[PDB]
Structure formats: structure tokens, C-alpha cells
């Protein structure tokens, strides 16, 4: 029985925690996962203080080659906007990318602003001031979210840009997805971006968003999968799944990655990391789905297995899978 440690992205933590629990019950293996944010996950795997790092923001082929890392996707989730708006219920407010960007830019300051009202004809929005909440830590959710905003709001694109950390024009900082959820829960008028599971498990209200094709879509496991249907995984695992075309494609969708060293110094550890994840691909789909994460098509899993065989080796050139 082995003891494994991973660290990183909080975006898929509920599901990694769930698979780890079940895995130990079935095999005795212990996987300790520390949700410290994607930036910390990358730092940690590079520093070698953990068996695997976890990041929602992919590293480029060159950065991977430079650090001797291999990257592979696990599940598909979505970022949603949790809101604390008195009198409104979950899923009732619709926002589009442009407006969402203006809220984050500080341009829109009240919930009954004309821009919001026009996207929500039937709604009676309070004249409550918006309290924007964002991540205090280096985050893959920030990356994904800013990647989205830069595509739909030109001003965001030009003044703040994209990144795990950016100069936020406004807002209170929350540490981790947990942090943002707690903030939104206690602040009337709050809006923060969290991975979907965090909104659901905390009973937070969330909004619908307008798809790239222009229709209001609700964030669901199936709508995350829908945004991923046209991804050409055979070309690369680092797919940009934000603002994708298609029927019911959630606009802020993202897969998330596991990073491991290609030249395993502790071959025994590396072998157990791959079994853990191979086990998760073969039997963990129902747990992912229970938490509203969409699974990767079997074809992508076979591609990952094929890449593990050609890329992960011990110091003697022997493959670990």
C-alpha cells in the first residue's frame, strides 16, 4: 500500500477527495491532496515536494519540456457566478460576457443597472450595490475566468488581460474556491466565480450565462461536456474550452490537469500515481458525475494511457506503465 501526495487546483478537489476516499477503501492506498491553488500546485511539483501537482491552467509544450513534466487531463467542470442577491433565486439571473466584464471592471455598480435589467426583462432587481469578490491566490479558476472575459470584453482584454493572477480593477479577495463561496454567502450583493460544485454544495445561487451561440444556458454537468464536444484532443490536451460554439455549451468550461515528472526518481511513487489515475478513469466516472464533473471521452483516456507508456520512465529508461 502506498502513500501519495498531490497539491494544487481546488477546482477539482471535491472529486479528487472523493476518488481518494473510495480508492483507500478499495485498495488501502492513501492519497493526500492539498488544495492550495493551481499556481502553488505547479510550484510544488517543480520543487518536487509532492508526487503530482494539479493545475487547471495548462503549461505549454515548451515549459513542460523545460521542466521535464508530462501533463494530462482528468475531468471537465465549469466556473459559475455565485451571487448573494436578496429576493432572487438560483438560475434566474442571466448575464452575458460583456456585462459580466463590466461588473468586474467596476463599470456596473448596482444590481438594477440598465445593462442587467435589459438582459432580465421580467426580473425586479434590487437597488443593491455589487460587491465583487475574486481570488486572492494564484488560481486556475482566475485563468479560465480571465481567459473568458478577455474574449468577450475588449476593455478587460486591454487593461487587465489574462492570468492566474492579474491586477483586479476592483473586488475583495477570497482564498481558494472555499474562500470565495464563504465570502459570497456572507455578503449581500456579492458576486464571485467558483467551480460549480462549490456553488451547489454551499447552496449558493448562481446565474445562467449566454453561450457563444447566443442562448441562455444553465451550468450543468451535461453543458460542461457540451462545451467539450468539438475539442480536437488528438492535437493537444491543452484545450481552451471557454466560449465554445454549440447548443447548450456552458461558456466558462475547463478541463484540469495533473502534472508529473517524466523521469521518475521514485519509480514506485510514480507507478502508484498512474494506477490511482488509471483506476479513476476506469471506475470513477459515477463519482465525478455525482459531483457534476463531466468525464473525458474513452478515446482521450486511451491517448493518455498511450502517452504514459511512451513518456513516464525511471532513470533507466524503463516505462512505469
Image: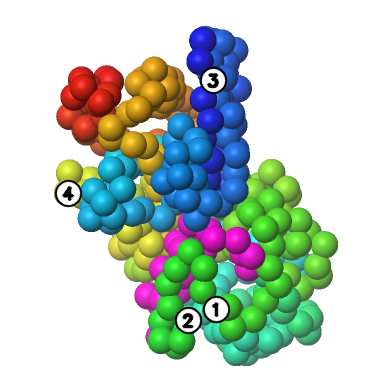
For this view, does 269 lie left or right of residue 172? left
Say which element carries label 4: loop
Which callout, 3 or 1, points at the residue further toward the start of the chain?
A: 3
Q: Earlier in the sequence, mark 1 or mark 2?
A: 2
Which one is in front in this view, the residue at disc 3 or the one at disc 4?
3
Q: Within 10 angstroms of label 3, few (less than 14), some, or many (20 or more) residues?
A: some
Q: Earlier in the sequence, mark 3 or mark 4?
A: 3
Q: CA distance from mark 3 to mark 4?
A: 34 Å
Question: Mark 4 and 2 residues: CB-CB less than 8 Å, in contact?
Answer: no
* Rendering coords of residue 125 (x, y %): 73, 78
Disc 4 and disc 2: Cα gap in Å?
30 Å
In this figure, which residue is indicated by the disc labeled 4? 235
First along the sequence among labels 3 and 2: 3
Residues at marks 1 and 2 touching, judged by CB atoms closer than 8 Å? yes
Residue indicated by mark 2: 160
Whole-angstrom CA distance, mark 1 to mark 2, is 6 Å
Q: Which residues are magenta?
A: 134-154
Q: Is residue 254 above or below residue 300?
A: below
Question: Is 215 left, or right, of 91 in this rendering?
Answer: left
Inspect this view and state whether residue 159 appears. yes
Q: Which residue is mark 3?
A: 3
Discs 3, 4 touching: Cβ within 8 Å: no
Secondary element at image label 3: strand
Image position, residue 273 (x, y; %): 42, 25
Amino acid at each position: 500500500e502506498a502513500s501519495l501526495t498531490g497539491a494544487g487546483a481546488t477546482f477539482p478537489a471535491p472529486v479528487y477527495a472523493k476518488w481518494a476516499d473510495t480508492y483507500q477503501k478499495e485498495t488501502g492506498n492513501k492519497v493526500n491532496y492539498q488544495g492550495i491553488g493551481s499556481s502553488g500546485g505547479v510550484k510544488q511539483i517543480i520543487a518536487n515536494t509532492v508526487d503530482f501537482g494539479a493545475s487547471d491552467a495548462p503549461l505549454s509544450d515548451e515549459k513542460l519540456a523545460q521542466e521535464g513534466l508530462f501533463q494530462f487531463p482528468t475531468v471537465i467542470g465549469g466556473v459559475v457566478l455565485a451571487v448573494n442577491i436578496p429576493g432572487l433565486k438560483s438560475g434566474e439571473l442571466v448575464l452575458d460576457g460583456k456585462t459580466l466584464g463590466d461588473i468586474y471592471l467596476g463599470k456596473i455598480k448596482k444590481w438594477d443597472d440598465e445593462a442587467i435589467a435589459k438582459l432580465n426583462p421580467g426580473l425586479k432587481l434590487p437597488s443593491q450595490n455589487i460587491a465583487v469578490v475574486r481570488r486572492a491566490d494564484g488560481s486556475g479558476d482566475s485563468f479560465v475566468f480571465t481567459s473568458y472575459l478577455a474574449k468577450v470584453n475588449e476593455e478587460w482584454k486591454n487593461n487587465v488581460g489574462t492570468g492566474s493572477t492579474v491586477k483586479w480593477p476592483i473586488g475583495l479577495g477570497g482564498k481558494g474556491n472555499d474562500g470565495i463561496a464563504a465570502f459570497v454567502q456572507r455578503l449581500p450583493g456579492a458576486i464571485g466565480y467558483v467551480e460549480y460544485a462549490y456553488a451547489k454544495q454551499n447552496n449558493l445561487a448562481y446565474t445562467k450565462l449566454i453561450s457563444a451561440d447566443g442562448k441562455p444556458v444553465s451550468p450543468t454537468e451535461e453543458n460542461f461536456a457540451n462545451a467539450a464536444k468539438g475539442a480536437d484532443w488528438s492535437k493537444t490536451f491543452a484545450q481552451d474550452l471557454t466560449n465554445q460554439k454549440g447548443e447548450d455549451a456552458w461558456p466558462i468550461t475547463s478541463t484540469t490537469f495533473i502534472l508529473i515528472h517524466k523521469d521518475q526518481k521514485k519509480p514506485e511513487q510514480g507507478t502508484e500515481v498512474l494506477k490511482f489515475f488509471d483506476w479513476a478513469y476506469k471506475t470513477g466516472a459515477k463519482q465525478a458525475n455525482d459531483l457534476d464533473y463531466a468525464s473525458l471521452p474513452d478515446s482521450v483516456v486511451e491517448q493518455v494511457r498511450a502517452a504514459w507508456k511512451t513518456n513516464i520512465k525511471d532513470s533507466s529508461g524503463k516505462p512505469l506503465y
